[PDB]
Image (cartoon, grey):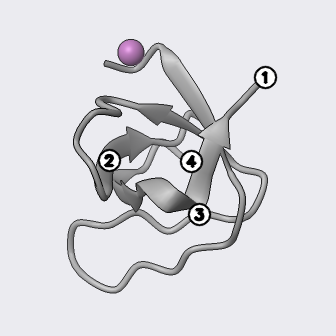
Amino acid sequence: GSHMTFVALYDYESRGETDLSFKKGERLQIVNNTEGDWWLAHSLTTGRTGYIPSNYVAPSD
Ligand code: NI
């Protein structure tokens, strides 16, 4: 619900009111990773929240 950390593979610029912008390499906490194309996430560095495209991220190890 926040204990899964993913890393951005590519930069992403938000296009609407609900999606989260991020940079390649940024770490994102995933609230739920079972939801398909859009995952709800937040950055611990910027604090910002929003939906991210699930094809833009991989697990952060
Ligand atoms: Ni969690």
- Sooner in the amino-acid sequence: mark 1 or mark 4: 4
Q: What amino acid is at disc 1?
A: Asp
Residue under numbered circle 2: 39
Q: Earlier in the sequence, mark 1 or mark 2?
A: 2
Q: CA distance from mark 2 to mark 4?
A: 17 Å
Which of labels 4 and 3 is toward the front? 3
Identify which residue is drawn at 57% across, 61% down: 56
Q: Residues within 10 Å of mark 4 (few under 14, many from 20)?
A: few
**Label 1 to label 4, Cα distance in Å?**
20 Å
Tell me the quarter of the picture where residue 27 sits. Answer: top right
**Residue type, mark 2 in image:** Trp
Tell me, yes or no, if residue 15 can be seen here.
yes
Residue that numbered label 3 is attached to: 22
Between discs 2 and 4, the one toward the N terminus:
2
- Callout 2 secondary element: strand
Task: Give the Cα separation between the discs numbered 4 and 3.
Answer: 10 Å
- Residue that carries the numbered disc 4 in the rendered image: 46
| Label 4 element class | loop
Quarter-of-image position of residue 18: bottom left
Name the one closer to the observer, 47 or 10. 10
Ligand 1 within 8 Å, label 1 CB: no
Q: Find residue 51 and report its horizontal and vertical position in percent.
A: 31, 56
Residue drawn at (31%, 18%), measured in percent from left and top? 1
